[PDB]
Amino acid sequence: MQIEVTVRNITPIFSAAPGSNYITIDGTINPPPGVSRFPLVRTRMMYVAADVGDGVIKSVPLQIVPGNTMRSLLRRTMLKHVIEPALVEKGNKLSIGAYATAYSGNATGNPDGVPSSFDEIATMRAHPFIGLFGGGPRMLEGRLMVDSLYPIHTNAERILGAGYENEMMSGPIT
RNA sequence: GUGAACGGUGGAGCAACACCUGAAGGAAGGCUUGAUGAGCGUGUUCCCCGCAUACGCGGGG
């Protein structure tokens, strides 16, 4: 089942791309050394194959938010005000490892190499929260598939599948 | 006139069949482009340093 959540950002988006990048006072991202470089945390960018001219496809930049950030955000909002109220209005007490595995998919950094029983797998994939986000010590596969947040941009023209032919941003978005 | 002289290791044959690199995972917490350099007081011959070599030049406060 496919969900397409079209959102519009009200304030600027800053998902910091890792990397020691630098900037001059008048632009010029990553200059040659000696022009008094300033530290610059660029926002997250996905390279996307796109139509640059008639019959030519090139790997253009397109500024996105990664799907891991979105996946943890969805996990965090359901945990913050659908799952934890369902546990503390009923007085249920999750363990600290249970809290760690709920909020981050694992309790420790060492998954078990042994597989879990099939009844356990069926119960957790039939579970409302654990079915969405798997993992755990025995590495359950979740049912949820969270894509990265692309903008409605012509650079993402091959991403959207021509679902939206309007509202297509052409110029730079940064 | 080498116990020599002469003498083909040959023909043919499938390394091949099947196999998910995969499950989970927040780039983030904090951070004034704002200044800084733009205008505001002294009223006449007093020390010391070099070039000279004193006829004078440059010069410290």
Image: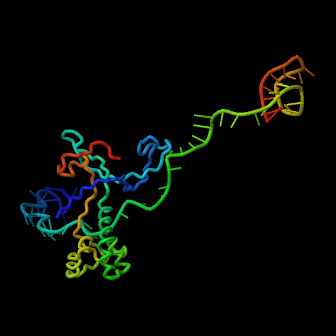
On screen, residue B52 above or below A3: above
| In-front residue for pair A121/B51 | A121
The answer to whether residue B10 is left or right of residue B46 is left
Figure label count: 0
On screen, residue A12 above or below A96: above
Q: Which residue is drawn at 28% across and 74% down?
A: A139
Quadrant location of the N terminus of chain A? bottom left
Position of residue A25 measured from the top left corner of the image (x, y, whole percent): 47, 42
Q: Residue at x 44, y 46 (%)?
A: A23
Query: How was the colour assigned to the protein in this rendering?
Result: rainbow
Position of residue B8 measured from the top left corner of the image (x, y, whole percent): 12, 59
Position of residue A57 measured from the top left corner of the image (x, y, whole percent): 22, 44
On screen, residue B41 above or below A112: above
Q: In which quarter of the image is residue A170?
A: top left
Position of residue B43 measured from the top left corner of the image (x, y, whole percent): 83, 27
Q: In which quarter of the image is residue A138?
A: bottom left
The answer to whether residue A35 is left or right of residue B36 is left
Q: Quadrant of residue B25?
A: bottom left
| In-front residue for pair A57/A87 | A87
